[PDB]
Each structure stands twice: as structure tokens, then as C-alpha cells.
Image (cartoon, coloured by chain):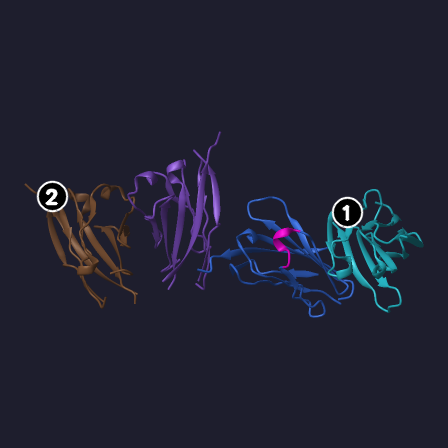
Chain colours: A cyan, B blue, C purple, D brown
Amino acid sequence: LEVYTPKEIFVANGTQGKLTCKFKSTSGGLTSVSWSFQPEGADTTVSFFHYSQGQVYLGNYPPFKDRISWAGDLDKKDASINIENMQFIHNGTYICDVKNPPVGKTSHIRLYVVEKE
Amino acid sequence: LEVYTPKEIFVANGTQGKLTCKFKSTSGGLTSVSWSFQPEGADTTVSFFHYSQGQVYLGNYPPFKDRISWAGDLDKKDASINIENMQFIHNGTYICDVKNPVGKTSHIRLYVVEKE
Amino acid sequence: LEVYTPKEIFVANGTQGKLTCKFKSTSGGLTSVSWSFQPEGADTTVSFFHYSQGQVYLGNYPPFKDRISWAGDLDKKDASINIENMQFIHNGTYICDVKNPVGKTSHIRLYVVEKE
Amino acid sequence: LEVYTPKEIFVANGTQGKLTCKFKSTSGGLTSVSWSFQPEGADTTVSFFHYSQGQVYLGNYPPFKDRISWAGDLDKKDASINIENMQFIHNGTYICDVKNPPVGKTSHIRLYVVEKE
């Protein structure tokens, strides 16, 4: 199992961010995706998205409320998500955790939200 | 791994349902719980709850909006959930899927009863 | 004691309707079942079926003549009945009354649908 | 609660039989009546009549089809019934089961149908 994420992305604030994850494995089925956020300059990460068995589940982290949508296809080995209307509180590191049975692999994105001016 | 669910529960409508799941295994850190609903008289199931790594994740099935809370403790081998203010649309079969390192599943037939 | 019926059922006309009742208690024996009919848009109810001690007893309500059969099992806590060849005169609310040593009641709103 | 039945009655065949039941209790609304038949020389009893909530319900026992009618009044503590056109197949023991919340008391009638000649 191999997981790719771009190292960094810059997103103009107020626009949609596309958090790309592509992975490599021998195989939908039992594979699961989880995304996590680590706010910049903080010590903690919040897991906010989980996908498995054709179902999207969301955490209750307020800054991501009504902003998160699935943009992947596990058959095409794509674990991506979109975040609407990104703002500065969304600066930080995003971490994708992919599990393909037969634990799991992770890749990090440093997301920079930029001033739209 | 072994998963238990009571075969049936009756919930007076307008009150809280307590969906009990107890499991048996040798270990809670890699353990995951999922809950599904099969509305009575349909053949679809909606997966609406997932728990792994100390985090509750919820699906967007409207009849469960703002009703679902975690009532378990994986260290105490308890994968239970609560559902607030149950109404007749919540009648059906609830399925708990627990994974330890594939899943084991147990079923509840939940009947919501007229509180009158 | 707890008594459950679905809130509603839709029965295509000319076909058999299956009136489900499931109950919860600590215990056949002295337990009894009665079913009643409230025709839509009237305020009368006719009690038309009674079950106690392995015996089905029927009332003399013409629209239910030769249509009613027991489909329960008090040991499996099932108090259901069947109604053959349901027509529009059978539209209304059905009420299951279950007694285990006063009783709880549950309601079905039964809609008979054009089979065309 | 106390329940009375006559010990025996003789009914000329082809005539109506009147199965008297009178009872004693402190109270009509929750009380129920049931009547049962034990055919002479058999070991089985068939329950064929039930009365509760102002409603008469009948069993499907063929010899009592279109023969059984309520002749009581629970307010007057009378749980009687009538049987039309009694024939020899109706010989036997009749049992009245009365229930009055606040479990029930029973009384037996040995009914002899007699040749009317």
C-alpha cells in the first residue's frame, strides 16, 4: 500500500480547496479513508472525515461544518475531499489515513490559505 | 471476537433508545464500531455512525440528525449508542459492526411503542 | 408489558393484509388478545377478534366475515392477525389490545390501495 | 367472586336450552365470560363463546354454528347463554368461566338433551 498527497497546497480564501489523495494497492471493499486536521501552531490533530462502505461520515469540528464533501473513488484509488469556502482558521496540516485490508498508511498536506486580494 | 446485541428493544416514542452492544476480544486502540439502520419494510440499510480512534463520525441520514450520541467505551468492550426522541420512522433493524484485528455483526429489532 | 404495531400499513385491494402485533412481557397462559376496527371517518369501534387459551373467537361484523385468521403465537409474543381480500370498506384504524396479568394497546392506520 | 351454575338441566331435543350463570362480585366493564363444552364421553373441552366489552365473540365449533346467543347482563351479574335447537350431539358438560378484575371462577352444567317424543 502506497499513499500520495501533495506536499503543499495554496488556496485563496473564500474558495474551495481540493485535498488530493491518490493511493496504490492490489484490489473499494474493506478499504477505508480518514482525514485529519492539525491547526497551525497547535499540538493536537482532529479527525473530521471517514469514508468506508460507500458511506461518508463527518466529525463535529465546527470550522468544518457544512464544508466537507467526498471527492474520491476508491475503485479508481482516489481518496480526495473538498473543503468549501476556506478561511484562515483552516490553515494547517491535513493528514489522509488509508487502510486497505490486509496497518494503514498516511500522507500529509500542508495547506496554506492565501489572501484573495 | 464476539459481538452481542439484545434481539429486541421497545422504546416509548418521544423517549431515548439505548442500543446496547457488548463484545468480547483479546486486547481498544485499533477497534472500530459502525452502526446501521434498516427501516422496517425496506431492503436497504443506511450506515449512520462510525467510531474509531476516540472520534465519533456521523452520517447525514436526516431522521438521525441531532439524535445520535456515543454511549460506549472500547476499553470496557462497550460499543453502544443512544438515539434521542425516537419516533415511528425509526422502527426497524439496527446492526452493529465491530472490527478488531473481519467484522462481527449483531442485530437489534427496535420497536417504537406509543407512549400513550 | 409493551405492545407494538406499525403506525401504518398499505394493502393493495383484493390482497391479504397482515396486521402485525409484537409485545414484550415476562412470562400463552392467561394472556389475551383483542383486535378492534374503527372505520375511517366514524367514531365507533367494532371489536371483532379475541384470542385466549388456544381459542380464536370472532365477532359478527359483516365486512370481516370469512376474512379473519390468527397469525400469532403467544409463546413467541406475537399477536398478529390476517385479513383476506381487503377492500375499501376496511379502511381505518385497527387496535390491538393485549392483556397480561389491564393491557396496553397499539394502533395501525391501515390504507387499502387501488391494485391497478 | 362467586359463580353459580345449576348442576344439571334437561332440554327436550329440538328446543332451546338456557344455560344459566349467576355470579357474585363487588362491581361490569372489566369482567369477561367464557363458555366451554365437553362432549359426553370425550376427554376434550372446546371453548366456543366469549363475552367482554359489550361484545359477543364465537368459536368455529360446527355443532354450535348459528345456535349460540348471549342472554346475560353483566350489570345484573348474569352470564347466561342460550342454545337453539338442541340435539343429542350437544349432550355433555358446559363450563362457565367468569373473570372479574380484581383469577377466575368456574361452574359446571351437566346438560341432558331428552327425546321430545
Q: Kindly identify which chain the residue marked by label 1 belongs to.
A: A
Give the residue drawn at x 83%, y 45%: A27
Amino acid type at circle 2 is Thr
Q: Is residue B84 left or right of residue A52?
A: left
Q: Is residue C89 visible?
A: yes
Q: Which segment did they paint magenta?
A: B61-66
The nearer-to-camera label among 2 and 1 is: 1
Nearest the eye: D50 or C103: C103
Q: Which quadrant would the C terminus of chain D be assigned to in this image?
A: top left
The residue pinned by badge 1 equals A29
* Residue B35 % position (x, y): 66, 56
Residue A96: name its quadrant.
Answer: bottom right
Q: As drawn, which residue projects farthest toward the top?
A: C116
Q: Is residue D63 above or below residue D92?
A: above
Amino acid type at circle 1 is Gly
Q: Is residue A75 above or below residue B27?
A: above
Residue D80: name its quadrant.
Answer: bottom left
Q: Which quadrant would the N terminus of chain D be assigned to in this image?
A: bottom left
* Residue B81 % position (x, y): 64, 62
Task: Let me know if marks 2 and 1 both belong to one chain.
Answer: no
* Label 2 to label 1: alpha-carbon separation: 79 Å
